[PDB]
């Protein structure tokens, strides 16, 4: 019994494959068109008339038609400090996150496990990602409790990473499944805006844009290598992963977990940073495959905001339809941070099937998934579609 | 170019190996024998002479001779709220962590890199663990900037997992190293008690024992598969990993990150709970190897408290020598959370090389590393030593 024999008989043989995808969102649906009226009223800023008009323009150009929020008029009426712009409110928000994050997360995981069709007891690893986690144990522990998974599921919680973490969990899931024979990784991203909601300030118009973009949602996947045919159904294959920090971007997107909750900073130069740095990311990802035409692959980009998508599109002269799946999710759910790119994969495989195309990847063969966040960090995931 | 082809050329070949280890602690060294006097004073509790007696009792049974603390008398003086039992202090604490966690971490990383000998440019992944992290980007990003690592180093932050995370970062590095050819992983655990320090209250003695046990420290590792002959020197090889949740232990160890900072709680039976489940963790790890004599392997156990070591030793009837390296770290450093097990690995290989033994693992071939924390969780890492 050498380390050699053990090592060989311990790893998996094939690439990490996404075998199921399920999503969930709080029940409360908030229409974008009339959110301003609602927001300024609930945050007692109906006098800030001049600033409201500014928020209306932000929503009207957000390219989002609705979002789902755990925060309701009733809940907010119960927590006035969360409605103020900058008041001590962390403890209240932590109580909300302790319950909703795992609840919404479980709901998505249940749909995913049901599509997968195998015993939940076969889940060997669990990755749970959220913008923040309120306590110790982290939310990965609470989700395992709710799901009733085996006590020995290997857990990894991914917290305070941010909007690019959808790529992060996929990069993490790829290695856990590829290096371990028989491993089946349940991946869950669950983001709830109770962590970021706050009143408006006619001084932080930069932060005000987060309130017009951020929505709630949870997305779950089952990832594994060496799919069992007649028992499992591959959706996408992961090929290669990368993570990088854009130069001259320190402070473009950051946050501070404080007594008043999670404060956030957004810079208007974010879309430019992403656009200026996207070609580089692609070359590194696709040149090895000998791919130069970026319209010959399917696309999944974190919809941080509509400008990021527009400028990436122009930069690479992408056909207008490349970003359809990404804009569809932005339109129906808003920016759900880490969960976005997972909803997009689901929308894409679903639309591809619904409409009888060649592969789950809009008929195309190769594809890419991008996550953007604090750093500014860029996560890259090369994917391969599956024949329908 | 096929995914199947890419996979084969993309993965590493052998077991993840620890190539270097370096540690660091704040300069302020606090002796345990006189801590009660210092503590009850800085926390204006001089008058509760009785509780000051109960703490001195705790510090005496602690088996800790001293600890290193970033928090100095002066600093606490500037931060009166951190010296209360439960007053709004999170914002003050975050400022401290934002600076010290990364500073101490870089200090340990630099030492690890020096032992290693290769350019830090060869580092491909970075795992940074700390009980908490103050903002977004997480401390992993800050460490990357401070060390001057390449901007495309793949990061993963391990936050709010707890005392068992020393095992967790080992479990993660193993998959990242083994599944990526050429991968060189910098692992860093950095823990600073500015997150947990608080005045005493005779109503939460479980919180008080935290004050007699928790110390500060950072430890760094370099992990990679396929060491380059006569350039890199292996220290230990990782063979197998596991993580499990002990039955009926929920509530034994937990915390809440709130406005008053991070609390800590216990159900005081933690020691029995670890003892009771340890054999089963050991069986699962070693039956597969025909090893049943736990005195025939080397030991690394997270020193949450002296009683845990005593009970594991009692129950397994281990020779007093087994827990020596472990108890020596607890003695000179106290409980540094996630960092402990890494300081212990360093102590074990040093003492083994110093006593002219045949392996880095006290002359033995196989060994075990145990991490324990919120959950209650038990992390297991099976190691193999290297001939010296
Ligand atoms: O449901 C959710 C949807 C989005 C978010 C975003 C959070 C966030 C936090 C930061 O510090 C910076 C930032 O750019 C974004 C959180 C929850
Ligand atoms: O330097 C440091 C060393 C150790 C710690 C430990 C904190 C901690 C907090 C919890 O809520 C639960 C727990 O199991 C541990 C903090 C700082």
Image (tube, coloured by chain):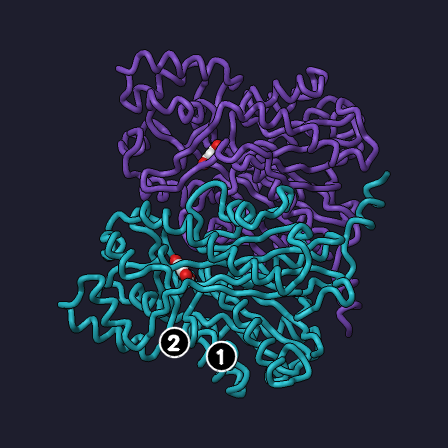
Chain colours: A purple, B cyan
Q: Is residue B257 visible?
A: yes
Query: Residue B353 at what x, y percent from top left?
Result: 63, 80
Ligand 2 rendered quadrant: bottom left
Asked if A96 appears above or below B209 in the picture, the reply is above
Asked if A1 appears above or below A162 in the picture, the reply is below
Query: Residue B196 at what x, y percent from top left?
Result: 35, 58
- Residue at 28% across, 20% down: A45
In terms of secondary structure, where does tag 1 sit? Answer: helix
Residue sitting nearer the eye, A261 or B187: B187
Asked if B118 appears above or below A309 in the picture, the reply is below
- Residue at 66% across, 77% down: B366
Marked residue chain, label 1: B
Alpha-carbon span between mark 2 and mark 1: 18 Å
Query: Residue A159 at what x, y percent from top left?
Result: 50, 45
Residue on which disc 1 sits: B312
| Mark nearer the N terminus (2 vs 1) | 2
- Residue at 41% across, 58% down: B192
- Residue at 66% across, 65% down: B19
State the quadrant of the C terminus of chain A: top right
Q: Which label belongs to residue B64?
A: 2
Residue sitting nearer the eye, B215 or B113: B113
Marked residue chain, label 2: B
Image side of residue B37 versus residue A96, left or right: left
Bin the neighbour count of mark 2 within 10 Å (Cα to Cα): few under 14, some 14-19, many 20 and up. many
Query: Residue B165 at what x, y percent from top left?
Result: 52, 60
Bin the neighbour count of mark 1 within 10 Å (Cα to Cα): few under 14, some 14-19, many 20 and up. many
Q: Seen from this angle, which residue lies furthest left?
A: B47
Quadrant of res A79: top left
In terms of secondary structure, where does tag 2 sit? Answer: loop
Image side of residue B209 versus residue B99, left or right: left
State the quadrant of the N terminus of chain A: bottom right
Q: Which label belongs to residue A159?
A: none
């Amino acid at each position: 019994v050498s380390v050699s024999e053990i090592r060989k008989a311990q790893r998996a043989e094939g690439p990490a494959t996404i075998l199921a995808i399920g999503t969930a969102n709080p029940a409360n649906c908030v229409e974008q068109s009339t959110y301003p009226d609602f927001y300024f009223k609930i945050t007692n800023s109906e006098h800030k008339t001049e600033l409201k008009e500014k928020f209306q323009r932000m929503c009207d150009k957000s390219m989002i038609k609705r979002r789902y929020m755990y925060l309701t008029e009733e809940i907010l009426k119960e927590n006035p400090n969360v409605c103020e712009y900058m008041a001590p409110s962390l403890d209240a928000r932590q109580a909300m996150l302790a319950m909703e994050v795992p609840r919404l997360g479980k709901e998505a995981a249940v749909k995913a496990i049901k599509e997968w069709g195998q015993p939940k007891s076969k889940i060997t690893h669990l990755i749970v990602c959220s913008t923040t986690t309120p306590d110790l144990p982290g939310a990965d522990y609470q989700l395992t409790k709710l799901l009733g998974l085996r006590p020995y599921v290997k857990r990894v919680g991914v917290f305070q990473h941010g909007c690019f973490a959808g790529g992060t969990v996929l990069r993490l899931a790829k290695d856990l499944a590829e290096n371990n024979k028989g491993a089946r990784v349940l991946v869950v991203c669950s983001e709830v805006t109770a962590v970021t909601f706050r009143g408006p300030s006619d001084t932080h118009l930069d932060s005000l844009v987060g309130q017009a973009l951020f929505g709630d949602g949870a997305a779950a996947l089952i990832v594994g290598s060496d799919p069992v045919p007649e028992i499992e159904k591959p959706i996408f294959e992961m090929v290669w992963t990368a993570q990088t920090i854009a130069p001259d971007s320190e402070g473009a997107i950051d946050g501070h977990l404080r007594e008043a909750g999670l404060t956030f900073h957004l810079k208007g130069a974010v879309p430019d940073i992403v656009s200026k740095n996207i070609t580089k990311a692609l070359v590194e990802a696709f040149e090895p495959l000998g791919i130069s035409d970026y319209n010959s692959i399917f696309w999944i980009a974190h919809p941080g905001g509509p400008a990021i998508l527009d400028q990436v599109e122009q930069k690479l002269a992408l056909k207008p339809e490349k970003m359809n799946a990404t804009r569809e999710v932005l339109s129906e759910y808003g920016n759900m941070s880490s969960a976005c790119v997972l909803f997009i994969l689901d929308e894409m495989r679903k639309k591809s099937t619904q409409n009888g195309l060649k592969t789950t990847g809009e008929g195309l063969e190769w594809g890419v998934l991008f996550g953007f966040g604090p750093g500014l960090t860029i996560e890259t995931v090369v994917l391969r579609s599956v024949a329908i």
